[PDB]
Length: 263
Length: 263
Ligand SMILES: O=c1ccn([C@@H]2O[C@H](COP(=O)(O)OP(=O)(O)O)[C@@H](O)[C@H]2O)c(=O)[nH]1
Ligand SMILES: O=c1ccn([C@@H]2O[C@H](COP(=O)(O)OP(=O)(O)O)[C@@H](O)[C@H]2O)c(=O)[nH]1
Ligand SMILES: OC[C@H]1OC[C@H](O)[C@@H](O)[C@@H]1O
Ligand SMILES: OC[C@H]1OC[C@H](O)[C@@H](O)[C@@H]1O
Ligand SMILES: [Mn+2]
Ligand SMILES: [Mn+2]
Image (tube, rainbow over all chains, first blue to last red):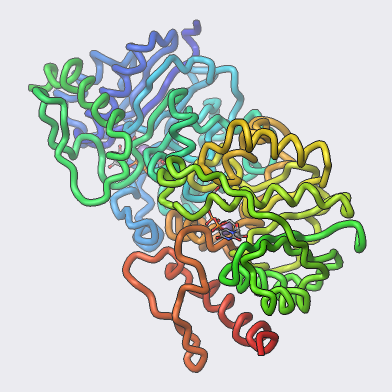
């Protein structure tokens, strides 16, 4: 229990705000004792900001930070993620002594308040390149020093992937090789692509999942959900449909807890 | 150092024996001072065993160990890997105090004799589920105790993925959470699939790669290579073709170094 520690998320538009809302709802569901904070930029509508105020203890307006790095973003095939540099504002939140940042496309499945036992920078390994941490869930300490060092590095050097993850890994470059206690178990940031890629591991370990992360171009809010049967329409090879359980949980929380505030 | 330490690989047939030949040639190219050993099973042809003896210091004949676990292997979509339990015989090699096991579908790009500074069990994270280690490159200590404990666990419990990686992860279950010194840098076991999945990380870190691992169903020896133009034919969506230079290097070593020994 601590009023000086928070979960922090980010939304730059009304689309990811549906994500932020479901995440915040899920953190209340599993009885967090910490504060809930969302960083929002001007493109979030006034009405949505009001809705965010019903779920989050603080809605904090910040300016968009955009890498403009079309070259590296294309290398990822995620041309829209330049605005993820806006995440660096999470370090300015000095009213808190420790925070957990969580992407707006994450969903909590159990209480995760034990993450506040960890020190900056604690994060889980990225399934793409596991000597990099995934920047969707991380434990950090707000700091005027670190905030400004991060903004400066972003201005001068940018990010190797055009978004927040590259520059955060570059700044926190010791992560792969020092202190194992700063490696969060993969169940605190379980990307649906690891479910597709090594299903045997998911079958043996996935019952312990604490956070699922709907990493990649297609987000839960882009699906067509039917509330009657509790199914989504799916195309092609969709790693989210290996264990569609998590996507359906996202939609059930959205439909019951969030949608009524929206329409 | 020279005499009581080895690199150890495995081949159960003449197909993977081509990979072992390239692997061994590559370890010689980079001037290892350790022994080179290959485990082989009766399906390997007599003529192919003779060729292996011209590259490896010793060819050690072992019995195939097969999980027969079609249900778990099907989850991976690798119905053929039950015979990978044969890898457990690497622990019987008590003529050596320390070994580095390397999958026959690996390729060495620089001297990696510094792996012998590591202690059992040291291995790189698996890109699919990075709280499991990839069993394609690992540092271990031959032991009659450990060998027999592994065979017993295999016989009574089997493997969660029907192959060696599940059982080795279960047996060495502390790897994810203890001693960061047992986490080998991902450059000592670089899956071609990580190049496709987070290409921006490969562009910044990939030049330091020491080992490449052609993990997955399609192996280098399944491609049609043209030696005249130094090209392969390939089909749509092939992670080996993101950075095809590793595949072409495999084929160049095979064509130049191994093909003459098969005469
Ligand atoms: O247009 C955008 C893109 C990203 N985000 C925020 O930045 C995070 C990171 O982007 P995303 O999850 O899409 O990246 P991925 O996890 O798929 O690589 C999101 O979860 C949001 O919190 C946002 O607010 N608006
Ligand atoms: O039919 C087989 C399959 C596997 N292997 C050996 O077991 C290892 C593991 O198999 P593989 O690399 O195909 O698994 P992956 O790395 O693709 O998951 C190979 O590199 C070989 O050394 C073998 O000798 N014969
Ligand atoms: O940097 C690009 C992206 O890399 C992966 C992380 O999940 C995400 O939060 C970040 O925005
Ligand atoms: O267990 C399945 C497979 O996973 C990848 C490992 O490199 C391989 O050796 C093993 O056979
Ligand atoms: Mn995300
Ligand atoms: Mn392999």
